[PDB]
Image (spheres, rainbow, N blue to C red):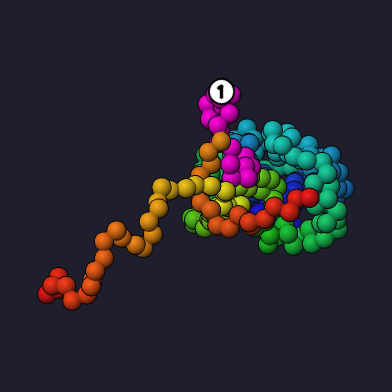
Amino acid sequence: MASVSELACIYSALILHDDEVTVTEDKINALIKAAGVNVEPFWPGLFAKALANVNIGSLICNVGAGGPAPAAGAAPAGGPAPSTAAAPAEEKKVEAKKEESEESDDDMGFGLFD
Amino acid sequence: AMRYVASYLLAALGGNSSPSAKDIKKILDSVGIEADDDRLNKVISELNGKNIEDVIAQGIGKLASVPAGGAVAVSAAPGSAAPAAGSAPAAAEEKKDEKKEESEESDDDMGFGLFD
């Protein structure tokens, strides 16, 4: 390899990608300083003033245009988990006569139909 | 997903073909990023002496940044207060006059009593 300039700037770029850190001139310059490489201030300056909102793979073609980046999201799930049932309920209703009546006759052929 | 790969690249491309995990950390910490020493050395020992010139020349994809894994974010399991057997409600000041009612649903009370 010989493209150390754009290499360092690109590695610095993607290292500053989307973390607790910010994609800024100071930060690329700091990473380049941290490694001890040589890149012309044009790359770090341009990169820091051009990126900061340019997803990630963008930097592969930032010299031409770039492009978007697809994303995804996770959806929660669950459900009801029943436990135990039924409880002793000793009740009693006041009833004496059952299926009977204190009046009964022929009880048949009554004119109550249409 | 990104790791410490481009940080290794920072070390190597810096002009020092000698993987100092400390210096990978140094590059991460230089600007203020929460890098972990174990994780970085582990990915470094996974990448130890691998395709450097290749990852440099045509490997601008998965390099270095937020360490892959997610590290728990917005996630929980449905495990709240365990329900009672079915009786004993949580009344405000349940301490006044023991009351036995409990009438809702009944389906077979076993109908026994051989307890002796």
Q: Residue at x 55, y 57 (%)?
A: B107
Determine whether B29 is above or below A78 in the image.
Answer: above
Q: Amino acid at mark 1?
A: Lys
The residue lying toward the viewer, choosing from A38 and B33, is B33
Q: Residue furthest bottom?
A: A109
Q: Residue at x 72, y 57 (%)?
A: B56
Say left or right for A90 vs A108: right
Question: Is residue A112 visible in this depiction of the protein?
Answer: yes
Question: Is residue A74 visible in this depiction of the protein?
Answer: no
Q: Chain of mark 1?
A: B
Query: Can residue B98 be found in the magenta stretch?
Result: yes
Return the x and y of residue A78 as percentages of the image width and height. 56, 54
Return the x and y of residue B58 as percentages of the image width and height. 68, 62
Query: Can residue B4 be found in the magenta stretch?
Result: no
| Count of marks overlaid on the render | 1
Q: Residues within 10 Å of mark 1 (few under 14, many from 20)?
A: few
Q: Residue at x 83, y 44 (%)?
A: B38
Q: Secondary structure at mark 1?
A: loop
The residue lying toward the viewer, choosing from B80 and A19, is B80
Q: Please state the extent of the stretch shown in magenta in the rendering.
A: B81-99
| Helix, strand or loop for the magenta stretch, by majority | loop
Dot 1 corresponds to which residue? B96
The residue lying toward the viewer, choosing from A100 and B36, is A100
Determine whether B92 is above or below A7 in the image.
Answer: above
The residue lying toward the viewer, choosing from B57 and A27, is A27
* Quadrant of res B76: top right
* Quadrant of res B55: bottom right
Say left or right for B87 vs B55: left
Return the x and y of residue A70 as percentages of the image width and height. 52, 58
Return the x and y of residue A65 as percentages of the image width and height. 48, 55
Q: Residue at x 69, y 33 (%)?
A: B32
Identify the image quadrant of the N terminus of chain B: bottom right
